[PDB]
Each structure stands twice: as C-alpha cells, then as structure tokens.
DNA sequence: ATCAATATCCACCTGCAGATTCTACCAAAAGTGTATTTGGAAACTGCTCCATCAAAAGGCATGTTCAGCTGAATTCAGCTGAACATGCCTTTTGATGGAGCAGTTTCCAAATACACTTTTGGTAGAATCTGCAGGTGGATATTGAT
DNA sequence: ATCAATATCCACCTGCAGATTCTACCAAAAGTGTATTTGGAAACTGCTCCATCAAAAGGCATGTTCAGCTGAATTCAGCTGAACATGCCTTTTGATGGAGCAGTTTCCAAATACACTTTTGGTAGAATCTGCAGGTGGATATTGAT
C-alpha cells in the first residue's frame, strides 16, 4: 500500500478550501438547527429561503474568521494544533468573553 | 440509536473543513465540541435580535432584512442581502 | 420656457443626485439638506463604486473568468489595503478568504 | 411597487471603468449593499457633525468633513476631490 | 451660560436608594455621560426601527423594542417593567 | 399646572426628554409615551447603577461616590459590565486582578 | 512675536518607569526590554489617530482650540467612548 | 548584611499598589508636550483646553493599560510570564487594530 | 538530491442551460416655476480661559552593579489525531399544491403638530457646611535570611 | 522552625477644598384651541414558503495503524529585576495680557412649500452568452527505497 504522511493532506486540504468559496456546513442540518434556535425565542416562526442562507453566510464567515485568529494563538505557544484553550483566548481578546 | 440535537447535525468533518479555510493544519478532538458551543452562541443572540425585528414588525416570517439589520446590530455587517 | 437637464449630469455624474437628495431628506439626518450635499455625496458614492469596480475587475480577469463574482470583489477589497479598513468589519457574501497559510505549517525542503 | 436599486448606476460606472467587463447578479448584490452602507456612514457622520455645532442644515461642507473622518488616507482625498469637482461643475449650471 | 444637565435628577434618585450617601462632582459628571450615552443609543436604535418599518413616528413601542434590543437580560427586563407602565400611570390620569 | 414627570411618578424630566427627541431627528414625529417610557428607562438605570455603586462607596468606608466606586460597580456587576464594556470611566481604575500563574507558589 | 520652542521628539518623555507603571496596573509581572519602544510605538499611533479626528472636529467647527468635546466626539467615533468630560 | 527582597516580589507588590489607585501614571507635562507636538504636526497654531488634554491622557492610559492585560494574557498563554513585543502584536492583531 | 511509481494537478477543448443582457412600455419620481420663510454668515464686542513665565523644591528618573531566576534550547516517551478504505444513510434535488400571510388600497378617528400665553422648575453665583486626603506613629503581617 | 527587616494596615487628627444649601431672575414646560396626517381596521389578493414525496449521491461515521507532536524534564547563558546614588525637571502657585469664544443683532442667500410637466428607472417577457460541468491527458509533487 502507499500514501501520504500526516499533515500533508491537511495542507492539500487547506489550499483547497481557501481556494473555494462554497458553503461548508450542510444546508438542512443548519436549517433544522436555525429554526430550532428560532422557535425557542418566538413560536410559530417561518423563514425566507434567502434569510437562511443569510444566516449560514454570517456564521461560516464568523467561524472561519474565528480563526485565522486563534491558529495565530496556537502558533503563539510554539504549537501547531488548535485547542479549546486557544479559542477562548481568541474570544477573550476580541471582547466576546472577559 | 441516533437521537441527537441538530447541533450535532453539524457533522464533524464539516464542522471543520472550515478550519482549513481558516488556515489550520491540525485540530484537537475537544475542539469540535468547544466549537459547536461557539457556533450556537453566535447565532443564538443574532436570531434573538433578528426576531425582535420580526416581532416589532408584527410579522410571523423572518426575512433576510431582519437578519441583516441584526448582523449590523452585532457589528457583523453583511453585504449581499439588502444592506 | 427652459426644460430638463438632470442635476446629476449638471454635475457630470452617473449616480442619481436627485434620488440621493430624496434619500437624505427622508433619512432623518437633519432638518434641512443643502443642494450641494446630494451632489457631493453622489460623487463620493460613484467614485467609490468606481474604485472597487476597477480593482475587482482586475482581479476578475486575473482569475481568467470574464465577469465579476463576489469572489473577485473579495480578492479586490482584501488585497487592497485602503479598502480593507473601510470594509474591515464588513462581510462579503460568497467571497471566501484570500489564500493564506502560515509559514510554520509548510513542509521543510 | 417594485423597490429601487443602485444597479444601473453601478453597471454604468462599471462599463466606464472596464468597458469590457460585466457583473454577476450577486456581485451586483454586494456592490449594492456597499453603496448603501457607505451612504449611511457618511450621512450619519455628517448628521452628527451638523448636530454638534448646533447648525440646522447639512451642507456639502458637512459631507466633506464626514469623508475626512471616515474614509482612510489617500482614498479620503480622491473622494474630497471628485466631490468638490462634481459640485462646482454643478453650480456652473448655466 | 445656561448649561443644563441631568445632575438634579441623579441627585434625586441618589437620595432615594442611599439616603445618607452623596456624590462627588467628578462622579456626578460620569453619571451624566452615562445618562446621555444610554439616551442616544436607545433613542437612535428606536429611530432606525421606525425607519425599517416605514413608519414616521417613534411610539413607546419603539422605545421598548429598542430597550429589548440594547439592554442585556434582566435589567432589560426590569426596564420594560419599570418602564411600560411609567406610561399607564401617565395614561390612567387625564 | 401639573408636570408630566410627576404625573407619571418619575424623577426624570419627561418634558425635556421629549424635547431632546426633537434634535436627534430620530424621526419626523414623537409619540407622547416615548418621552415618558424612555425617561423612565433612564431613571431606572441611573438608579440601578447608583445602588451598586453606593454599596462599593460604603464598603470603602466613604460617604461620597467617587468615579472609582462607579467603576467597581460597573465592572463587578456583570450585566452592567456588558452595557458599559466599550466605555471608559475617567478616574476609574481597574478591578484588582492578578493572574493565577503570576502569584508566588 | 514670541515663538517657541520647537517641539520635537517628545515621545521619549513617556518614560520607561511610567511605561512600567501602566503595565503593572495592567497586571504584568515582568517585562521584556523591547517592550518599552514597542509601547511608545503603539501609544503614538493611538494618540495620532485620536488627535487627527479631534482636530478635524475642531476645524470643521472653525475654532482654533481643540475642546474636550472634540476629543470625546473623536474618541467615541473610535468606539472608545469616554465618560467624565461632557458626553 | 543588608538586603531586602527577591526578584519578582516587589513586581506583584506594585501591581497591587497601582490596581488599587486611580491616579494617572504618565507625567503631565511630558504628556502635554507630546500631545501638542502631534497636534501641531497635524494642523499648526492650535490651542487646547486643559480639559481636553486630560481627556486625552485619561483615554490613553485607559487604552494602553487595557492592552497590557490583553498582552499579559498572551504572554501567559505561551507559558511565558514576561510580556514581549511578540505578545503586543498578537493582542492588537486579534483586537483587529491593524498594528 | 535522483530513480521509479503511485497519486494529484492543471491547462487545453468544448457545447448548453441557466443566467445575463437586451428590448419594449408605464406610473412614479424628479425637475420646473412661482411663492414664502429662515438658518447662520458677517460684524462687532464682552469676557473667559489659555499661554507663558518664574521661582523653589523635592519627587522621580537615570545610569550603574550584581545575581537570580526566567526564556530557550535539547532530549524523548507516549499518546493523540491524521489518513483511508469501508459501508451504510442522511442530505440533495426537482417540482409541486395550497394555505398562509405579507403587501396595499381605501377610509376615518385618534393622535400630534403649530402658535401663543401663563406659570413654574432649573440654573447660576453667593452662603454655609464638613467629607476626607495626608500625616502621623503604633501593630500586624509578610518576607527572607540563619 | 526562629528572628530581623520592612511594608502594609489602620485608627485618630484637622483645616480646606469641594460639596450642600439657600435666594433671586429667565428660559422652558405646561395649558388651550385650532390645524393636519397617520397607522390602522376591514377587505383582498399574489407569492413565497411549508409540508410532503422519492430517487441516488456521494458524504459520514467507524475502525485501524503509525507518525509525529505535544508535554515534560534538565541545563544554562544571560537578561531583567531590585537597590542605590545622583541630579534633573516636573510640579506648584501665582501673576497677567490677550487671543478668541461666544453672545446678540442684522440682513441676505438659501432652502422649503406647493402645482404641474416631463423623464427615467424598473418589470416582465424576449434575445444573447459564458463559466460550468466534465473528459481527457501531460506535469508537479510526494514517498519509499537506492
Ligand atoms: Cl399594484
Ligand atoms: Cl425651584
Ligand atoms: Cl492641622
Ligand atoms: Cl471655594
Ligand atoms: Cl472549469
Ligand atoms: Mn450644499
Ligand atoms: Mn388654572
Ligand atoms: Mn513637528
Ligand atoms: Mn501540460
């Protein structure tokens, strides 16, 4: 059998998705998730098709951008692996949490 | 025996294929849960502000403008949906 | 009897000076709107439209595609440094990120 | 009935800066949101300018200071320019 | 000449909750800024609500959804409370 | 003559608050409940930070609220933290806080 | 008819001990030697950007004195809203 | 025969001293000159309300201090205990200030 | 770095539906014309509030010495997470039917806008009070050395 | 574990600045009566948006193996902290001349308020096009063995 050593598809994968522009969470898992989060605020809500992609767009953006910002924090600590410890530092500096 | 909140419908590979668009070589196993947490907070308070817009307008359908006004409200101004 | 020249072309603009005026009156921005304000602004909006439009089209043809997608407009705005701040806390739908990998992540030889 | 947009003006100015370049519909979408935002910021910042100084009206003079505050660097000045340039050309409406 | 403040009202409300506590002039200052800031945000957020809904007036309802939007959690909730019927006490007299 | 502010059982000047809605040009028109409801919210809020602050005034063994105390108030109370996160209180100080790892041990 | 004296290089008046003092209040136990210049680096950008806006407010208003309001209006504009000076 | 304290120990001692106070930490006349200089270099021939300088100095010290803790979190994140430029740059980059 | 070998990319070509652009008419803006109203620019000018200035002092910065403890560097085991084939399933996709609602005309009652006229609450200096900052010296605690 | 060396706490004092109180003149609510729009409340559609519905597609979970990474542990050079002596410069205070707000008044230049006349900006069909969606086949990269 022969193959690629750990980390290398990752780069191959990073360049692929940075190359693309497509949505990455899937639509109906999201939609389901969205309406659920919605119903819990006001019952009897329905949604514009457009208003859901609006939310996927905002989220995927937020999240991806959530880091480049920590990957910097993982790298800041002579590491190459992102850990929860890292995300929290990202959000704490941004001002999301303390 | 798959009874599981749709937050977990945010499938694992898919949770972060994103991380790569985000420029990440490799990710901890804990990261996914922690992530699913942040995903949900982010869109919770957004839908909360979006919805009061839907509600102030005495409507029962959330429109993309409600989303947009709300994203802006949160300082996450989104272009391509009406403002 | 002397008839119509749009005020937008009296100012040599593509952007609608008249409309912008209507829009400033109806924005609750102040009690009165001077007649120069909407021309000046329309110019500024037309100018700014122009500036991201050329920088984007450049990146559009660079991508070997005939027209402009949101992709290109992103590549345009994020690669340009002066537009990056004007649009820093703004998110472009269907845009993507600029390709960027940290030095430390790459293979070695 | 139908709403109104900036797409013709954007498409026009587009044909002028790149005669051989169209524009995608959602790219037109973005461009539309862009004008709008910028519109508000300027209009807002001027509105608030006008108000600090207890002046009742917004002049081109306020719109300018607005641009000065809110547009960055050199992009600020081609902006003050193309604006005072559009405005004198207007007042020469003979 | 004629500068006006909210400082009497703060002093009033100060003797209500801490009858034997007083307030320094620089602390009183800060309280004003607090009042004034809180004032535009609410008044502003109301302003664009009316505007999103194409209606020309700000009613108490706008001031409210405003409060709902901009105050966090429980002081948002004690506000609408303490607030919604500052207004009937007003409309139940004539 | 009876003023609207006490007519609604408020300390804050409903009358003025109405007038101050005159110049934001917040809209063409101002409903008569708007200044009442709002002036109430302001009175509510000044009140709320005033108690939490006075507490810290009296923890500190002082009769008079310094901006300091107002800071200790705003930052230690967490819902008030958030409404005032992006605001700086002049002459305020920080909350006393040392990082765990920094302490000798 | 009395103009003086040239103001030049006043950034170094932000002394290392003072940079220290700010840093302790920030809760910092130990500081690299490079930190001080970097800091002066960051301070001066910050203070430029604010004073640039403060002043644009002063001139639009056709005054030749920067007033605290101008400062405040400018700080707020930066999203660093300051309480205790007039708004 | 004579000594007092070990390294690091007064450091904490002053952290507690300054976190307890509210005084401005930059000196007044040095700050003012700098201010006047940046100003003058921006538009000549300006004057300043005593009031508007403190406005700036209050605002500044607030800004800088707030970054320092953000910095300190970054130093402690990297198993270090001393702040370095490497830290401040990370702080401002995440803040989004654009270093 | 090269040799040989899976394994992945990347231009070169290409014909088509799904979009983009172009054409062909209609209310709704925008533009005019004539009529009034007003906000704020010029022109004094009263009066703060700024800019220097000086003297003396003592707080605080600077520069130097000395060592401790921090940052960084190497080594290394072990355990975590990447890589993949594998196999089953949730998601996609393509219309579709029908109720559900947003979008609007039309039409008045209620709510708010003007314009004055009293009437009163808020403000600005002057009149009294009186917290608390700063200076103590006495105690307790903390720190660091034997 | 004791003992010296500071430093931190903390209670009491006390004259002063900064707070609190008290009086008197004016801008600002409030009160009336008449003058104008609005935001529904009822009556009606178009259009999206929900609920199903059903074939297949790849996508996801799962389990296995190994690599390399992260976390730990040690050693060490050197950097940064603590202490001091030295001495500059900020801080204080108090005075003073003047630039420059800001407070008033006066009078255009400019904006708004209506009334009609044109013109354009935007729709829904009708007429053109290009990335794509996909099939190659030629190179670049990657990997394990020499
Ligand atoms: Cl219709
Ligand atoms: Cl009174
Ligand atoms: Cl004494
Ligand atoms: Cl006094
Ligand atoms: Cl293709
Ligand atoms: Mn004008
Ligand atoms: Mn009566
Ligand atoms: Mn200079
Ligand atoms: Mn080839």
Image (cartoon, coloured by chain):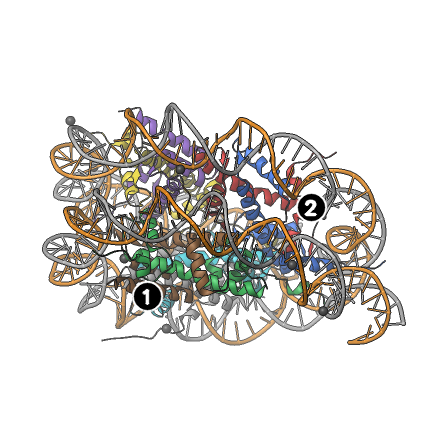
Chain colours: A blue, B red, C green, D brown, E purple, F yellow, H cyan, I orange
Comparing F90 with H23, the one in front is: F90
| Picture quadrant of ligand 6 | bottom left
Q: Is residue I31 left or right of residue H30?
A: left
Asked if residue A52 can be seen in this view, the reply is yes
Comparing I80 with C96, the one in front is: C96
Up-down relation of residue B1 to residue B15 (above or below): above
Q: Is residue D34 left or right of residue C95?
A: left
Disc 1 to disc 2, how far (Cα)? 56 Å
Question: For disc 2, does the CB lie below 8 Å from ligand 5?
Answer: no
| Residue ID for mark 1 | D85
Q: Is residue C76 left or right of residue F70?
A: right
Chain label for disc 1: D
Whether discs 1 and 2 lie on one chain: the answer is: no
Density class for disc 1 (Cα within 10 Å; few <14, some 14-19, many ≥20) is some
Q: Secondary structure at mark 1?
A: helix
Residue E12 in percent (x, y) is at: 31, 36
Residue F48 in percent (x, y) is at: 40, 37
- The quarter holding residue H37 reads bottom left
| Residue ID for mark 2 | B12
């Amino acid at each position: 059998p022969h193959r690629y050593r750990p980390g290398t598809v990752a780069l191959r994968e990073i360049r692929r998705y940075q190359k693309s522009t497509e949505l990455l969470i899937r639509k109906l898992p999201f939609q389901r998730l969205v309406r659920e989060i919605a119903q819990d605020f006001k019952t009897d809500l329905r949604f514009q098709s457009s208003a859901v992609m609006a939310l996927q767009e905002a989220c995927e953006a937020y999240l991806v951008g959530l880091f480049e910002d920590t990957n910097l924090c993982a790298i800041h600590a002579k590491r190459v692996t992102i850990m929860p410890k890292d995300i929290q530092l990202a959000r704490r500096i941004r001002g999301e949490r303390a | 025996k798959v009874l599981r909140d749709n937050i977990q419908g945010i499938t694992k590979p898919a949770i972060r294929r994103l991380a790569r668009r985000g420029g990440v070589k490799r990710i901890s196993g804990l990261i996914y849960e922690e992530t699913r947490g942040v995903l949900k907070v982010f869109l919770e308070n957004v839908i909360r502000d979006a919805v009061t817009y839907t509600e102030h307008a005495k409507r029962k359908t959330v429109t993309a403008m409600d989303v947009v006004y709300a994203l802006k409200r949160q300082g996450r101004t989104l272009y391509g949906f009406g403002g | 009897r002397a008839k119509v020249k749009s005020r937008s072309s009296r100012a040599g603009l593509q952007f609608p000076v008249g409309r912008v005026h209507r829009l400033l009156r109806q924005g609750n921005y102040a009690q009165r709107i001077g007649a120069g304000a909407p021309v000046y602004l329309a110019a500024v909006l037309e100018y700014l439209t122009a500036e991201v439009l050329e920088l984007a089209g450049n990146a559009a043809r660079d991508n070997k595609k005939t027209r402009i997608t949101p992709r290109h407009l992103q590549l345009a705005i994020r690669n340009d440094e002066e537009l990056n701040k004007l649009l820093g806390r703004v998110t472009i739908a269907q845009g993507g990120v600029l390709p960027n990998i940290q030095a430390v992540l790459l293979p070695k030889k | 009935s139908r709403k109104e947009s900036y797409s013709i003006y954007v498409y026009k100015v587009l044909k002028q800066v790149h005669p051989d370049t169209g524009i995608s519909s959602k790219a037109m979408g973005i461009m539309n949101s862009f004008v709008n935002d910028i519109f508000e910021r300027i209009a807002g910042e001027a509105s608030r300018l006008a108000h600090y100084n207890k002046r009742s009206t917004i002049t081109s003079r306020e719109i300018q200071t607005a641009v000065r505050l809110l547009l960055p660097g050199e992009l600020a000045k081609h902006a003050v320019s193309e604006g005072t340039k559009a405005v004198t050309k207007y007042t020469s409406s003979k």
